[PDB]
Structure formats: C-alpha cells, structure tokens
Amino acid sequence: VVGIGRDKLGKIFYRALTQYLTPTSNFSQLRAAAVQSATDLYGSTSQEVASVKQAFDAVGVK
Amino acid sequence: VVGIGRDKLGKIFYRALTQYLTPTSNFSQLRAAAVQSATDLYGSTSQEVASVKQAFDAVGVK
Image (cartoon, rainbow over all chains, first blue to last red; front, side, top):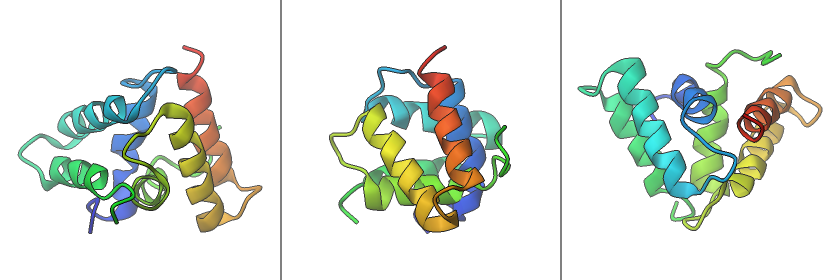
C-alpha cells in the first residue's frame, strides 16, 4: 500500500494543506508539507512518514 | 463545513497523487486531482468534493 491504509493519510494531507502549504504551491512544497505533517502527527519513527514519501514516488509513474 | 471528517481525505489524496498527478505538479493541478478523486469515490455533488475544495480555498486566501 503506497500510503499506509488510504483513509489514514487524511490527517497528514489535510494538515499539509491548511498549515504547511501555499496558494503558489508546486509539487515539492506539497512533499515537504506532507512529510512534516506525518512527522508531527504520528512521530518520525513511523512507517506513516515512509508511506507519505511513497505516495510522491508513484505520481504518474504508477 | 468539512462534512466527511479528515479521515476520509486520505482515500482522495492517494488516488490524486498516484493516478491523477504529474511529476511537474502545481497547486492548481492538485486541486483538480483531489476534486476528481473525490468525484470518482463519492459522486460529484458530494460533501467529499465540497470538503476537498474547501481545503484548497482556505490555503489560496490565507
């Protein structure tokens, strides 16, 4: 699973938008925002961060 | 009114990244990707689409 267990990504991504993201966002801004979000929500010793990272990998290159 | 609960938001963003997004992505590209994910998942005139849009809309104003 390329993002933990789909629905569980919710917390990370929502936070990544409303706290870490900008109106003038690119792909990389999202990446950092999402990793930071995961790190804060579930700790960084977690596969939850690794899963956030994994999402970015398979973007168009499925 | 993010009427789905942050946990549902995860389903969307996995699909948004891996199936709908580009390597050379931007905020506007992501808007569509997430909205479209939510459409596929929960119908078009859906609270899921409403909650997704709202996230992007808040970010875009500050």
